[PDB]
Amino acid sequence: EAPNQALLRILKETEFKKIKVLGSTVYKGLWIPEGEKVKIPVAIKENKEILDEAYVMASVDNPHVCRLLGICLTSTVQLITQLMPFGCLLDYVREHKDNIGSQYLLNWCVQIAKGMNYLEDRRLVHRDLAARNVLVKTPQHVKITDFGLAKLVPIKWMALESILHRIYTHQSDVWSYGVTVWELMTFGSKPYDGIPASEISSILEKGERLPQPPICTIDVYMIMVKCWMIDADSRPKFRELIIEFSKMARDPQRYLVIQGDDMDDVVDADEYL
Ligand SMILES: COc1cc2ncnc(Nc3cccc(Cl)c3F)c2cc1OC(=O)N1CCN(C)C[C@H]1C
Image 1 (cartoon, helix red, strand yellow):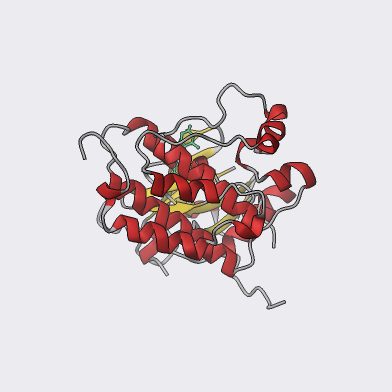
Image 2 (cartoon, helix red, strand yellow):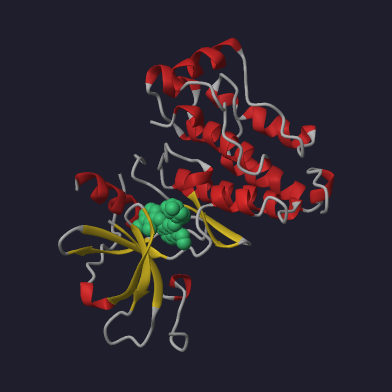
């Protein structure tokens, strides 16, 4: 009901340099706003769908969500955004599975919940929350991205009511939050590995759920289980998840049990306002 006064910035292609490939296309590069004396590390993602994505990314502004810097309209529609140098959190947990402590895991849970609470504040349902869609700015700071599915298909992350009746709500996102947390606490295991997507709705209806990760106390796993209640309004709210994971982050070893616990003018997008 409130007007969306977000600014869509159209960026000249001549302001982008050092373009190199990250995956397939998404590239890294440098954005030098003309007449600004600043170099900004960026990712660039290479039509109604990409622009629906650009619409949502330009309309968010929160420390735990990735925002659109602008678009470039040359041969292709390119989305320009802050470079998140450590890549996706799923690949990060898998590679550093032996250097990741309780403080980091719980802090990431708090930050993802903050991002999702903000989206709820903005009446946005993400619909694709997953560890592959959280990026790592630094090991201390992650942010939610990939809004090409958000509104005002990944079966193994979806609430049962979404699989059965294509019903999507903030509380359906809470279910996906629970699955994302399970991915982190297993250092990136695949949910329901080897179980075909077609059989997922059947398993969930019988009462089966993802199992307790070895490092998780019952305190942490019980929160995960609450996100998978059949009654959507019985699941936690994101603002409650922030609270509970914050409490646990003050004493992380009580809640997770882990054995062993081009440079002069560079400005990060978070300091470029
Ligand atoms: C350095 O790594 C990355 C940093 C990113 N910073 C921002 N956004 C990124 N994506 C993005 C998402 C939505 C909208 C826009 Cl506009 C985006 F630009 C980033 C992607 C990155 O790359 C990966 O995570 N990799 C890991 C290696 N695989 C091969 C896969 C490949 C995907």
